[PDB]
Length: 81
Image 1 (spheres, helix red, strand yellow):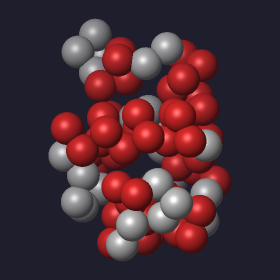
Image 2 (image 1 turned 90 degrees about the horizontal axis):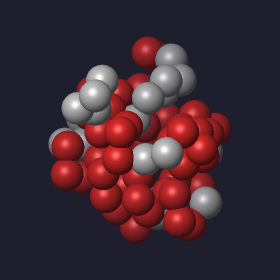
Image 3 (image 1 turned 180 degrees about the horizontal axis):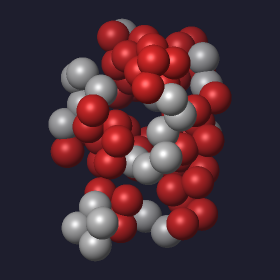
Image 4 (image 1 turned 90 degrees about the vertical axis):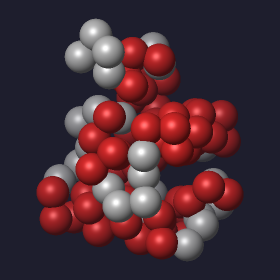
C-alpha cells in the first residue's frame, strides 16, 4: 500500500472522497463531469454488489476506471463535494 493510489491523499482527504463514493446517488455523482454517464451507474452498482469502497485504489475494480482516470475523478470529488 506504500505504492497505492491512496498515498497521494491525506487520510482526511481520502475519507472525504470515500464518503461521496459510498453515499452519493447517480444523479449526485453526475455533477462531477468525469462521472457523467456510465461511470456514475458503475460506482453505485459496484458498491451495491461488492460493498462500500474502503480505499480509493478499489475504484480500479470498476469498469471504465483506470489509474489515471481514478486519480482525476478523486481530485474532482475532493474539491467539489
